[PDB]
Length: 402
Ligand SMILES: Nc1ncnc2c1ncn2[C@@H]1O[C@@H]2COP(=O)(O)O[C@H]3[C@@H](O)[C@H](n4cnc5c(N)ncnc54)O[C@@H]3COP(=O)(O)O[C@H]2[C@H]1O
Ligand SMILES: Nc1ncnc2c1ncn2[C@@H]1O[C@@H]2COP(=O)(O)O[C@H]3[C@@H](O)[C@H](n4cnc5c(N)ncnc54)O[C@@H]3COP(=O)(O)O[C@H]2[C@H]1O
Image 1 (tube, rainbow, N blue to C red):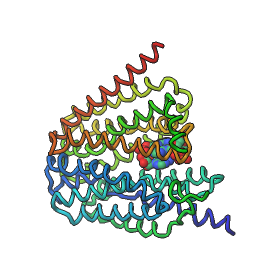
Image 2: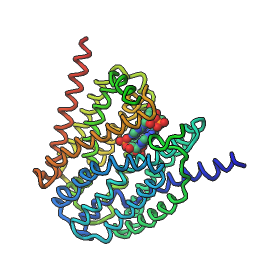
Image 3: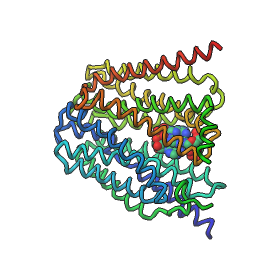
Image 4: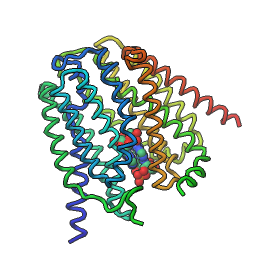
């Protein structure tokens, strides 16, 4: 039966690749592996030389991987994302120098640029009458797969007492299997821009006059340029708060699973907020950004190794508060946008957020710029979120006055 094969062999394989491609158990523990006894990097060498090229190359590969995903019909970039995740874990386990780890974060930004591959693959594959059910099953498989990767990464180092190098070998076994699964993915017969089955500047300029598309895209290019700077460097900060060498009380996987679990809760709890709290939208940003300005300052202030579990809660609540706004951000941006225009508005919001993130990494974090340590960067990121929270708060009172 063609309808029965379309669910028992294609949707069940879409969700299985959506589950298995997220399984990287040693992904939360990359930075304790770099700063551990195995690779033996200095904390001033990961913060200022290895991690700022995670933002440099992400600016370099965002425009190619956005165009090569639509031109190659979304499957070989899903194969390239698996083949770049292998090259990350190969350079983790075979590279010893800093240029190998700057090449490791080069390929890690190709995987970050190809996160747009899988969610836009389900759109061009599935018929639009059955798309929202398959995409609902597919996003519920990458949500379970991201959560159970960090749980499996946490249960091996803590319950199993597995070393970090043996964890990255288990993570290589789950990643070459994700390359094999990406070869058997059904290629879609259409795409969004270059391969269409069978104006956009006119539809953009009309929708650019919307008060919520201009507000929440200016949130996207400044708050996500500061959200993605904390999540690059909070694993270097936890190696300054509690610089342990146990590899069993590291707990970076439980903080990346609780930020997925709570982040899915606030993502779901923001579904009732996308339409109701839509006019009070500059005050809703300013309430969350000031919460993000205090949680980053709480990360920047905590220095005792006994208080490391305050730094885990100050990051789960940080990612849980950012994931309260995305739901509201993507709804108000993509409310009256065409789907071909929605992929380009989010394609330039993610690009201009990378433009800002490249500016702040070169000034604050890079050794060719200033080269601040990771505790002094987080004081600068806290004052970045504070002078951003008062801009939307003054905007909530300038428009609240009228
Ligand atoms: N409309 C929405 N409703 C509820 N939650 C939302 C949401 N949009 C984003 N989130 C949450 O924000 C996180 C990062 O979003 P970002 O768009 O910057 O980076 C995204 C984006 O580049 C891409 N992506 C996700 N969904 C997409 C979609 N429907 N269409 C195109 N690209 C998508 O994957 C990355 C991470 O997605 P992931 O969900 O694992 O992680 C997402 C998700 O948990
Ligand atoms: N992180 C992201 N990066 C770039 N673009 C993004 C994005 N998240 C959503 N978009 C785009 O915004 C459109 C409307 O988002 P909405 O949140 O209202 O309704 C969304 C949202 O509730 C949900 N959703 C989308 N991405 C999600 C994610 N990463 N995690 C959980 N739910 C997601 O699917 C619904 C329709 O998605 P669809 O693609 O057909 O249409 C989506 C999608 O193309």
